[PDB]
Image: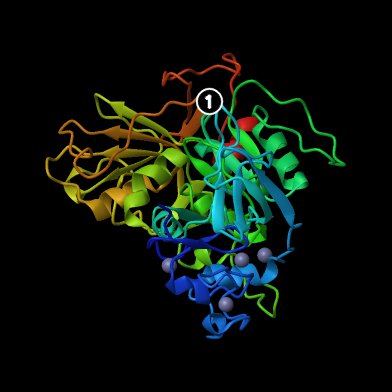
């Protein structure tokens, strides 16, 4: 009992290209013949039963199939003896209608009486297509649109895991992906004119798109805008996809072809951040539609048990300002290397203020939060960095190492010195 590839209804018939169809859809598949009850193709007018004409496609599948040539296969004899035949297992049209050659321990089983039958095999073209699954899986998929510049390649590397599968359209894109991953599984395709490395034993699979679905945990689609539309539908019939694409420019002058599914897929626009690290981007994400990707290093986050004066000090209320400290409201549109979020007063912090305070610093932020009130507004875990930090403190240069100790030496630890301020740079040398 087979179901229709279009609508999922019971399917007694099939297209020559391997699509199971219900009675209704026997007459809306212009791609190739559909042998119906009278033994002729629907709409052929070979007899009076097949005179009603074919209708226009009811599915995007039909539009996709306009670029997929039907090549009629050879008419081959199927020899039958006690329900056994030499022909390969599959599905065939015969004078007794559509029949299946099943694999078995005794042999290739076929439910037909002894004889010889002229047989045309169904092509594999739409053997794995299921448009009700495509619809469902499209909803549970995502299309990651990249930014104008770079970074889209590095998003994938942070997301990919050893159990995952990455589908890619060409030999070259497959090679590009394999080089970017470093360690991955694959089978070098026959006939290729590229120099493929050796495949690893572990890592994500890199599969050529034309090869079709193979099982995995998460499935990705590389170069989505370049991919074969029918192959994409084959995948979406079996799994959901994370589909990677580039920034949509205004080029359409017949210059844009991509699978229709991407225009109805849930979309995620990537945005490059140059001001602070990824850990900050993650904490602030709830306030933004775009997925924020840091194109710079991790911003340090340290939870001090006692007050401190590193970099610019920030605090909600004027009452708690000391020395050259400012309010969080006064810090809007200002940028620093180091910042100290000073929160002595209970219930003094909301989302808006906290968002401003967290997004001022470039390299480090120290948070004095004795009331533990930042937790109730933000998820911001403590993050260290193996770096030698440096900043002024009331007309006096000072430096702190990776373990947040006030060391005053000349490059003793042997770590990097991160700083972007005008005064900190020039004073650093001399
Ligand atoms: Zn149907
Ligand atoms: Zn067809
Ligand atoms: Zn007919
Ligand atoms: Zn790529
Ligand atoms: Zn394209």
Which residue is at a point 48% across and 26% down the rendered structure image? 385
Question: Compared with residue 235, is residue 38 higher up or lower down, i.e. above or below?
Answer: below
Classify residue 32 by image quadrant. Answer: bottom right
Would residue 14 appear left or right of 302 to someone viewing this image? right
Task: Determine the secondary structure under disc 1.
Answer: loop
Quadrant holding ligand 1?
bottom left
| Residue nearest the viewer, comparing 274 with 67 | 67
Question: x and y percent of residue 104 in the render?
Answer: 55, 31
Would residue 278 appear left or right of 345 to someone viewing this image? right
Instruction: Determine which residue is flagged by label 1.
Output: 387
Which residue is at a point 58% across and 57% down the rendered structure image? 18
Question: x and y percent of residue 5 in the render?
Answer: 47, 61
| Residue nearest the viewer, comparing 284 with 219 | 219
Question: x and y percent of residue 185 in the render?
Answer: 65, 29
Crowding near the residue tagged with mark 1, few <14, some 14–19, many ≥20 C-alpha atoms within 10 Å: some
Residue sticking out furthest to the left: 346
Which residue is at a point 60% across and 22% down the rendered structure image? 202
Residue sticking out furthest to the front: 114
Question: Compared with residue 325, is residue 200 higher up or lower down, i.e. above or below?
Answer: above
Question: Compared with residue 259, is residue 385 higher up or lower down, i.e. above or below?
Answer: above
Which residue is at a point 50% across and 72% down the rendered structure image? 26
Would residue 15 appear left or right of 398 to someone viewing this image? right
Kindly tell me whether mark 1's CB lies below 8 Å from ligand 4.
no
Question: x and y percent of residue 150 in the render?
Answer: 63, 51
Quadrant of the rendering where the C terminus is positioned: top right
Classify residue 53 by image quadrant. Answer: bottom right
**Do we see residue 163 in this rendering?**
yes
Residue sticking out furthest to the right: 193
């Amino acid at each position: 009992s087979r179901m229709c590839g279009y609508c999922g209804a019971p399917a007694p018939y099939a297209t020559a290209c391997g699509l199971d169809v219900c009675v209704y859809h026997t007459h809306f598949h212009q791609h190739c013949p559909v042998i119906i009850w009278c033994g002729h193709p629907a709409g052929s007018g070979s007899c009076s039963e097949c005179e009603p004409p074919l209708g226009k496609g009811t599915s995007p599948l039909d539009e996709v199939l306009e670029q997929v040539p039907y090549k009629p296969p050879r008419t081959v004899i199927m020899h039958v003896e006690q329900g056994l035949t030499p022909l390969d297992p599959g599905r065939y049209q015969t004078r007794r209608g559509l029949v299946s050659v099943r694999r078995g321990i005794r042999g290739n089983e076929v439910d037909l009486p002894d004889g010889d039958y002229a047989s045309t095999a169904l092509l594999p073209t739409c053997k794995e297509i299921n448009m009700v699954a495509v619809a469902s899986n499209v909803l549970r998929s995502r299309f990651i649109i990249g930014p104008p510049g770079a970074g889209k390649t590095h998003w994938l590397l942070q997301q990919v895991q050893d159990g995952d599968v990455i589908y890619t359209p060409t030999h070259q894109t497959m090679l590009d992906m394999i080089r970017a991953l470093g360690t991955c599984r694959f089978n070098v395709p026959a006939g290729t004119t590229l120099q493929f490395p050796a495949p690893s034993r572990t890592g994500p699979w890199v599969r050529i798109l034309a090869g079709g679905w193979c099982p995995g945990k998460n499935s990705f689609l590389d170069e989505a805008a370049y991919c074969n539309h029918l192959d994409v539908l084959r995948l979406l019939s079996k799994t959901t996809l994370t589909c990677l694409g580039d920034f949509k420019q205004l080029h359409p002058v017949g210059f844009d072809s991509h699978c229709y599914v991407f225009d109805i897929m849930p979309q995620t626009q990537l945005k490059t951040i140059w001001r602070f690290g990824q850990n900050i981007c993650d904490a602030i994400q709830p306030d933004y539609r775009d997925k924020l990707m840091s194109m710079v290093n991790t911003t340090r986050v340290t939870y001090v048990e006692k007050p401190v004066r590193y970099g610019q000090v920030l605090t909600p209320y004027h009452r708690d300002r000391e020395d050259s400290a400012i309010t969080i409201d006064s810090s809007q549109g200002a940028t620093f290397d180091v910042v100290t979020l000073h929160l002595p007063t209970k219930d003094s912090l909301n989302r808006q203020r906290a968002l401003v305070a967290i997004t001022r610093a470039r390299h480090a932020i120290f948070v004095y939060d004795p009331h533990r009130q930042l937790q109730s507004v933000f998820d911001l875990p403590a993050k260290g960095t193996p770096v030698n930090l440096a900043v002024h403190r009331d007309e006096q240069l000072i430096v702190l190492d990776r373990n947040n100790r006030e060391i005053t030496v000349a490059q003793a630890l042997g770590n990097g010195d991160k700083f972007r301020a005008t005064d900190k740079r020039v004073v650093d040398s001399l």
